[PDB]
Image 1 (tube, rainbow over the protein chains, first blue to last red):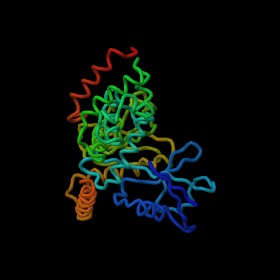
Image 2: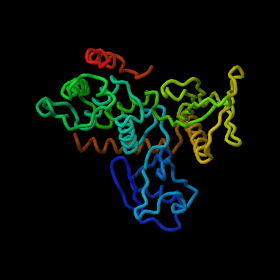
Image 3: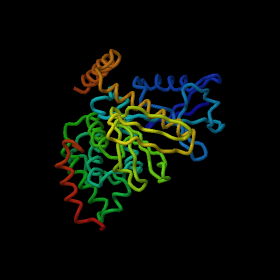
Image 4: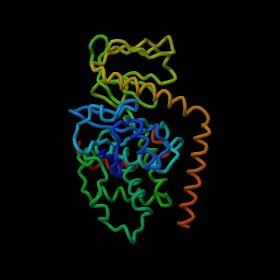
Amino acid sequence: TVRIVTMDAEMEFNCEMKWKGKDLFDLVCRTLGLRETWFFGLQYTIKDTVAWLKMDKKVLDHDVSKEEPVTFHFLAKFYPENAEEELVQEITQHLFFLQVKKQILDEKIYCPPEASVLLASYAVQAKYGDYDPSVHKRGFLAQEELLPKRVINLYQMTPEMWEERITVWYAEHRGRARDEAEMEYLKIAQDLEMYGVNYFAIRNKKGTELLLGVDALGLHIYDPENRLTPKISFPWNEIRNISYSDKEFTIKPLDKKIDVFKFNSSKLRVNKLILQLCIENHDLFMRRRKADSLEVQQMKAQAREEKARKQMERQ
Amino acid sequence: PKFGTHHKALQEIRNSLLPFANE
């Protein structure tokens, strides 16, 4: 018995014994009606280690616990550069909105205080629809989790004062349907420095502890105390080659004036994950810079028909 | 630019919060 946890739902599947990661993943995506499968994965945690279900491996053969309800979390593994230009289906847009809002509220990704207020105002518009002073009276947001605790702890303001500031901006969002408000939330969130960045502990050749960030834009090297501003960045289209051999990675820039960057990473399983994230992020970087495939063109036409079908019922 | 068309609102929010900073 396999339990699948999405950002807003829990499903149970009667998984076959001789089934591989691909079979379970495809079933989940079909059940959800999700066609942009390339962004997503099935994640699990064992003995303090985050891992993804391998598509070419048997589900039961994985290092996951042999607990009665074998559980995976369906989550986005890859992120678009501009969600407003790339995410086609409403289901995909909504799952990204939920996941990213959770990363902001639980402080997985940093957010300046002013952005947390503006983001909360779009989350309120998405959840409640248009602000209406007859309905949304003072105290209507008292039970909502609106801001990261880090932000609340930086100011001498009451919950009512935070609600008032959020409500001012919520009132400015009149006219945004749920999908429009959730997409405006993603448009703000996707410009945060930590958005979509996968961090890994590495060392340079002199032993200096650093972090590698793998993201939709390229590769980035950080001092461990500052995950916001890379010391050096290598955009995907500026990398000539990435080599890996015996725990050592080498990033070779296309620009000869930029030095080759070598670093080490201690865990083989993590190194395989770093390489997988490099290959697929580089592939997605190239794909979004070329004209839509016929499959994407048709997916957009179908999403347009679905949006117009739902709009006819409301009007 | 960072935060696209929301710079004006972000700066106004920054100004509204400033008097209450813990420091």
